Length: 354
Ligand SMILES: O=C(NC1(c2ccc(F)cc2)CC1)c1ccc2nc(N[C@H]3CC[C@H](O)CC3)c3nccn3c2c1
Image (tube, rainbow, N blue to C red; front, side):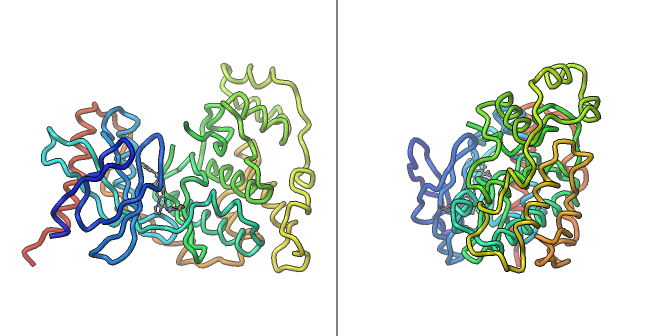
């Protein structure tokens, strides 16, 4: 059947081996962790995105990432998190296991492309509201992202927004000071990243585009200002010296960083205001996380709260199957077995004698 026969297609320098239900494959990314194709799903009669994770067990980092992705995509079912349509491997044993394919509903655009548009307050607010909903949903299951960025967020033609991944040529620009400086963190680490996306949406420029972490920290302090001694005292001694030795900067007020001229044209009497967006930016782009807003407070902010719906913002938490995502270490072979088991568990949840 279309659901049990495989065929192979060359996509650049890689072979995609997928169920025959998936037709007319066309590359749509990516780099670093694998390739993603658009396809027509002849059974569902609609378009899908198919990503190939090549040897996700190759090392601890790829492994723990692939595993988290499979488990979370499966147990989450939320408007603002990409859903899992199908998962499979073409290889027929643990010994032979190489590749995992994950199938998602195809979305029309990514957020990088949407950010480049001339947006209005209505759509900026709604996109931000949805990002905050997705983030809060993950946080309710104890999942803290740390690496939200526009290339990993997709958007439908009707503005529905979905986050594609679950957290941390790799893009460092959206990572919080906690991350840059190797500090402890809490949930509002993700709110820094939202601030960076929001800032970029407004000014059509990456806010902190460092070539590395040194350059990125420099751009943070040059624009927001050197943090206060109370923050400095929170740094572990090995990092505090570096931070305290940088040249000192006063930074710019948010009225200087984000003046009215950057906001939508002819929008002085909209329901939402540039001053509200600027106020929210000023509470998310706060170096000291203990002074930065929480997600809940962001959802209640005047720029965002227009859209507030408890079914989206107070949804029942995802149920992560018992102890499945604990802190434990595993060998590469152990990770390989865990990921194979997760792929095969998908079949076990579908097969029936009716
Ligand atoms: O899974 C995706 N990216 C990640 C990834 C990709 C590959 C991989 F091996 C491991 C992880 C970070 C998760 C991904 C990338 C691009 C994705 N691009 C999509 N749509 C395109 C938006 C831009 C348009 O120009 C063409 C369609 C789309 N619709 C549903 C899911 N997606 C996409 C998912």
